[PDB]
Amino acid sequence: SMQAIKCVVVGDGAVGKTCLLISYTTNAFPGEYIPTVFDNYSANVMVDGKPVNLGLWDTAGQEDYDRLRPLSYPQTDVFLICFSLVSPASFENVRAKWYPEVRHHCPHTPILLVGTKLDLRDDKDTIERLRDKKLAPITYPQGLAMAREIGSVKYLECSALTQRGLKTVFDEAIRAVLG
Ligand SMILES: Nc1nc2c(ncn2[C@@H]2O[C@H](COP(=O)(O)OP(=O)(O)O)[C@@H](O)[C@H]2O)c(=O)[nH]1
Ligand SMILES: [Cl-]
Ligand SMILES: [Cl-]
Ligand SMILES: [Mg+2]
């Protein structure tokens, strides 16, 4: 027994959940091949001088799985609720959909709020695209405020593509369970 930790990742379609898991576990961002299946990834992580077995559970974010997806929730040690920093709709869904759904099935499990696609937040074409819809990328203070609102233990931002902040997401996830 390496200590085992079950981590489940949830959030809207296209927020980057699968890329996040693959980039983390393989140290490589998927190119033109992102698994469509909702797999479980097994990673090992050193925490305070001890190896931990992190099982990472990908989920489908579409409405069609609203009855099937929660069957993966039992025995979860920590949830990651993901939204894209460059999709305000995905951010609103953290409060509207994901927080309520997780808490319906798992009242006490820690939640980390994770803002993805960090590399796009200061990307000009992305800012302009959002400005056209009277919108702007989600800022760190906004994400932090959403994290408090949903009782998250931690708010993190990362990019699966550049890997900036990626390892911290899962270190903090583990520490939320273990210390
Ligand atoms: N620029 C950027 N694109 C990303 C990142 N992570 C994922 N993507 C892209 O976002 C899209 C959705 O990613 P995916 O992992 O399939 O999202 P999922 O539906 O939540 O599983 C794909 O086109 C990815 O290439 C990131 O960190 N930066
Ligand atoms: Cl999805
Ligand atoms: Cl917080
Ligand atoms: Mg996926």
Image: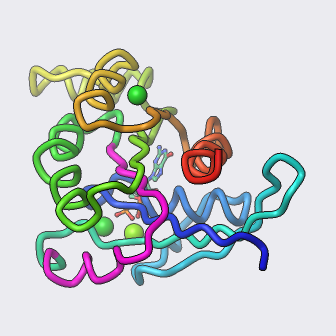
Which residue is nearer to you in this view: 146 or 60?
A: 146
Q: Is residue 119 left or right of residue 129?
A: right
The reply to whether the magenta stretch includes residue 69 is yes
Q: Which quadrant is home to the C terminus?
A: top right
Q: Position of residue 95 (x, y in %)?
A: 16, 42
Q: Which residues are magenta?
A: 66-83
Residue pictured at 75% horizontal, 64% vertical: 52
Q: How many tags in the picture?
A: 0
Q: To which quarter of the image does residue 127 belong?
A: top left
Q: Per the image, is 178 magenta?
A: no
Q: Where residue 7 sits: x, y (%)?
A: 50, 64
The residue drawn where x is 23% and y is 57% is: 103
The vertical placement of 111 against 133, above or below, is: below
The quadrant in which residue 37 appears is bottom left
The image quadrant where one finds ligand 2 is bottom left
Up-down relation of residue 114 to residue 36 (above or below): above
Place of residue 116 in the rendered image (x, y in percent of width and height, measured from the top left):
43, 42
Image: 123 above or below 92 = above
What quarter of the picture does the N terminus occupy?
bottom right
Looking at the image, which residue sits at the far top?
141
Q: Nearer the viewer, residue 107 or 124?
A: 107
Q: Nearer the viewer, residue 132 or 27?
A: 27
